[PDB]
Image: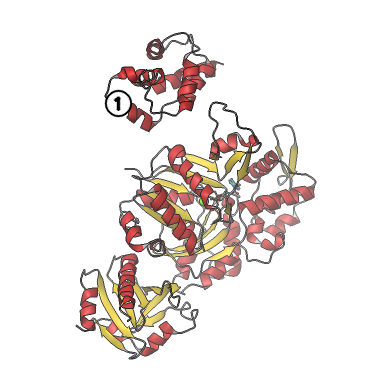
Amino acid sequence: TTALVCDNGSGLVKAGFAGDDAPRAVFPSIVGRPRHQGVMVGMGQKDSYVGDEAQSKRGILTLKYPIEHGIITNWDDMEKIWHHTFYNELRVAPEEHPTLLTEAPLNPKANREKMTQIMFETFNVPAMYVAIQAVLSLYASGRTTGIVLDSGDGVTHNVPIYEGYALPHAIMRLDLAGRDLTDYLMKILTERGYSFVTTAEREIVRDIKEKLCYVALDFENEMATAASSSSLEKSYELPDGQVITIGNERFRCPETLFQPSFIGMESAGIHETTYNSIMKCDIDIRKDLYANNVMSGGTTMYPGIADRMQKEITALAPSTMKIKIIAPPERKYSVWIGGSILASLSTFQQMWITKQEYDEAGPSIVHRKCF
Amino acid sequence: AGWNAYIDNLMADGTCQDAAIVGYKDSPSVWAAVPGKTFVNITPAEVGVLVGKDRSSFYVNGLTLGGQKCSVIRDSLLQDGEFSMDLRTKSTGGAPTFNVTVTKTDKTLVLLMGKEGVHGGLINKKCYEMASHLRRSQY
Amino acid sequence: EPKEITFLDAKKSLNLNIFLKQFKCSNEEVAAMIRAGDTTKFDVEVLKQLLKLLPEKHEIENLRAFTEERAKLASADHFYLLLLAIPCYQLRIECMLLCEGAAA
Ligand SMILES: Nc1ncnc2c1ncn2[C@@H]1O[C@H](COP(=O)(O)OP(=O)(O)OP(=O)(O)O)[C@@H](O)[C@H]1O
Ligand SMILES: [Mg+2]
């Protein structure tokens, strides 16, 4: 039987079958309830809408984004999202397909235990495995040992992996991602002169972040030519006719990943958390950490992030002139694609958690099979 | 029936290559171990590394068990609910690496060294069942 | 009256009855024309309403598991079982709706 892979994202939950090149379902991490009061019949309107149906009818719906910074806080809405993800998005029953799952790094243990007990008691899966998004992100590149930068919509993390097994001591957290970049992009486009108070304006700024924004090889040099660059200044058309012009901000929104002092916090960047996370490991693994550095998430689609990661790791680490930072073109879904690669293999059949293991061991099996 | 019967109970299914009941209370020494293997040479200095209050030194280069260098992955050992310690054997030059579980009972230390290709989860659950069985018997 | 046993909620049978009663014919002529591929009574909105009321997999399995006498079922279930007797009907309905919508 074919397996199911879902990436439970902070901003985009993806779902599909194992072995597929692309996820079949990509829907935002939203649960909508009807905004106004009114009952009638109306040929049986649903009490709750999730996903693409929630996106489509979103004017008469109040939405909820229940994942805050990678970490699950509201659990019933995750249960409703997982019920949509199985029963209508893929149109399956979860009691015969083994289901691979994703966790944010530095997840609390009670969250993993609650996640496992809701998979085994409510949905009653016959097999489930929780993987860190970075481990699947390394599996999409096709290796088993190395450090991986993963920045999604919730939170940025740098995770070292040894033979498929992560090291939770040297995982480091940077408290920004594509939602925080989106908020900063509304902030500096408002400083440019615009205003985004509505829903559709926020979606247009999200698509501006999708299309136009990039990372330069040098921030200071591209500042130095910013007034004089004829190719830097882009723009975008809203469908009702509003025009949004963006200039140097195209490489100020993702450079918040490289320098978080742009927005006003003193946390270390995506290259500095990577370097500090490499030094917190054992010494022997660190060359394999530099050799298999994979960036992942939709927050790494900015063109020219590869050579800037190269130059920043070149600046911090004098041993890393020639090693290349691997950037797959499909690293939007490298968590999902690596989950497809991991679940589709015939070597993964032992690593699944059975129902009887949860029954005899409790929820704490997630501490001991998923490591 | 002595502690050698407890080692033979740990060597029942054949999934683990070495077992150790090592005292840290009352009589701090290796009470029993598999003869000829690594864990028979556990010093009380390595026990003091294990039971010591500093839970951040051993992350720099691993620690030693029976003279064998190993890397810590998880540390929940002094915590009363979990009492668990996950390690992997370090090796030089592509030599195969092995999974290690260390647990507290009330009086003893249960250490388990697994075989090649054997997952650390089975080692962990077997050692947790052993530690819970010893703690139920006030050991 | 005999009990109209259905494997569906009242919403989907209600929308299918409001859909079917506008056409002024029984369900046999509807399914026989869906097999025949006639586009006279199918415009874009009617085929959109037909694809909006597609059967679910457990509903198809429940209708296949019903080995009793067919007379006690509802007329909507009679339409569903007449629809299930057509080989490759859903792709043909998609072909007709995509052809009419493409021309539009
Ligand atoms: N082409 C793109 N360029 C830039 N940003 C993008 C692009 N596509 C999506 N994004 C943004 O990046 C994020 C999507 O990343 P991703 O799918 O990895 O996140 P997630 O899985 O929801 O998050 P997390 O892994 O923290 O749970 C969103 O904030 C989205 O707006
Ligand atoms: Mg994700």
Q: Nearer the viewer, residue C13 or B75?
A: C13
Please tell me in which quadrant of the rendered image residue A144 appears: bottom left
Residue A248 point in image, percent of width and height: 73, 51
Residue ID for mark 1: C66
Circle 1 Cα neighbour tier, 10 Å, few/some/many (<14 / 14–19 / ≥20): few
Within 8 Å of ligand 2, the CB of disc 1? no
- Secondary element under disc 1, as helix, strand or loop, is loop
Residue A135 point in image, percent of width and height: 45, 58
Classify the position of the N terminus of chain A by image quarter: top left
Residue drawn at the location 39% of the way across and 52% of the way down: A121
Describe residue B66's horizontal placement relative to residue A366 as left or right.
Answer: left
Q: Residue furthest right?
A: A193
Q: Eyeballing the image, is A85 above or below A149?
A: above
Describe residue A144's horizontal placement relative to residue A1 as left or right.
Answer: right
Residue drawn at the location 45% of the way across and 55% of the way down: A115
Label 1 chain ID: C
Residue A185 visible at all: yes
Residue A136 visible at all: no
